[PDB]
Amino acid sequence: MATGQDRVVALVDMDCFFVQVEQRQNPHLRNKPCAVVQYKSWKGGGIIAVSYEARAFGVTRSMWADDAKKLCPDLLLAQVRESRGKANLTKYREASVEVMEIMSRFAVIERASIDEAYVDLTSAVQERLQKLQGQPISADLLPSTYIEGLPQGPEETVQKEGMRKQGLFQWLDSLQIDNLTSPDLQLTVGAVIVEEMRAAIERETGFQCSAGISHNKVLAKLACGLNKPNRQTLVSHGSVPQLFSQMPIRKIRSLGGKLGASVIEILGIEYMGELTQFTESQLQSHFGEKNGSWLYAMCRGIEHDPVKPRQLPKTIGCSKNFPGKTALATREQVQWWLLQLAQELEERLTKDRNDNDRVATQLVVSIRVQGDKRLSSLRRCCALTRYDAHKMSHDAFTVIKNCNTSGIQTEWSPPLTMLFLCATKFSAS
DNA sequence: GGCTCACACT
DNA sequence: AGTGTGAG
Ligand SMILES: Nc1ccn([C@H]2C[C@H](O)[C@@H](COP(=O)(O)NP(=O)(O)OP(=O)(O)O)O2)c(=O)n1
Ligand SMILES: [Mg+2]
Ligand SMILES: [Mg+2]
């Protein structure tokens, strides 16, 4: 029986990342309840990131700033840059690149989002094990590490840091240093490397982050969120049974949506651990061959999804919603906004070509019409042969112009509630 | 609520 | 090629 203990995988995720970017730039924001917002004019702006100090007051990502102020009167705000009537996330993408570049020094990474990346530490661990061969691992090498499930059995325990240490001590005391093979030893050395990586990030960028270390991406991601912020968590294969016994299905990556809901509804269960009851065939019959096999393995802590060697996004896109009364109702209006989106896209693509030695070859245009529940009413694509904003916007209109319901042709019906331009199908240059 | 991304399915 | 789900 395979135990899925073949790899050491880590997930590193920045703490309150957009807030940290603004806090680094503006020292007045440091160590205070603050949030990052976009489009200040409406209800003070929509919050997209929240500092831990602000989270203590109950401020969340969903909220309008005016509403967040009601919970947290002293809340400080930082505004996302606005360009061409649109939120521009350039500052945060550049900050992301800073972090990713540092991580790449230690190992090959998969960029999972703007503020997180998976790391395959398997090779690095082998090397490190040989280098310090026969040498026991000190607790001092793991100053911010939690061992999930520990401490166990028999006032220091009254304080969080006291508990962390006791668990770490119990873990280390148990490790067999000899035996380079031991998965637990491999995860431990993995955590040592992650400590160093996290230290390099903070020293060179000033940003703090949390991390998870386990044998696969799903567990690594789950581990990461266990002790945020500014801490890392090691989830061993052995900790899985107890961990999953009370773990809501929706917590597992990819189960947070309809699929997760269907697992709960069809099987009549609540926790990830209860999945172990069912045969692989049973799971496949309900949720399909691929999903069924994945679930059967996952509830036992086993997953084989590889850490893909990809540091750069596959697509570059910008979009804007025009909700309610703001929906675009004229041909001229639609064309003007297409131009704004195309202009920002051109800037980003030009930088991309210079920085990354690649060119996009396909242009995708997506729109939403008023009254449509679907996020995208229509998607169409055309060739992208020139990095020219006017051509791109002109081409995008050509592709969608037939969508217009109205006879006048100076007026657009139904009104458009969303425009989206995306460059794809990159090739080396 | 808003701006982005990746990927499975057909 | 075009649609839908999931996420951060
Ligand atoms: N729905 C979302 C989720 C995240 N983001 C952005 C803002 C976040 O700061 C950044 C990182 O996402 P996130 O890791 O899930 N949360 P954040 O980093 O702010 O706080 P942590 O919980 O990770 O400490 O992406 C967004 O713009 N819209
Ligand atoms: Mg984060
Ligand atoms: Mg994140």
Image: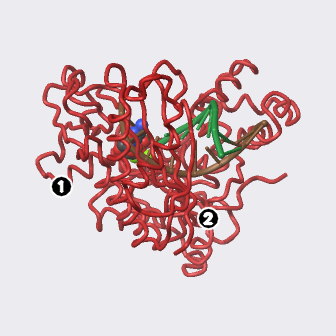
Chain colours: A red, B brown, C green
Depth check: give the residue in front, A317 or A196: A317
Where's residue A240, x and y in %? 65, 42
Mark 1 is surrounded, within 10 Å at the Cα level, by few (under 14), some (14 to 19) or many (20 or more) other residues, namely few
Circle 1 marks a residue in which chain?
A: A
The disc label shown at residue A150, or none: none
Depth check: give the residue in front, A299 or A328: A328
Depth check: give the residue in front, A219 or A107: A107
Task: State whether residue A149 is above or below residue A312.
Answer: above
Q: How many marks?
A: 2
**Residue A267 horizontal side relative to residue A225, left or right:** right
**What kind of residue is marked 1?**
Gln
Where's residue A336, x and y in %? 32, 41
Where's residue B3, x and y in %? 37, 42
Q: Residue at x 75, y 42 (%)?
A: A294
Ligand 3 within 8 Å of the CB at mark 2:
no
Does label 2 lie on the same chain as label 1?
Answer: yes
Find disc 1 in the rendering and name its residue. Answer: A25
Circle 2 marks a residue in which chain?
A: A
- Eye-nearest disc, 1 or 2: 1
Please, which residue is most extreme toward the front here? A408
The disc label shown at residue A186, or none: 2
Q: Residue at x 38, y 26 (%)?
A: A411
**What kind of residue is marked 2?**
Gln
Which of pointers 1 and 2 lies earlier in the amino acid sequence? 1
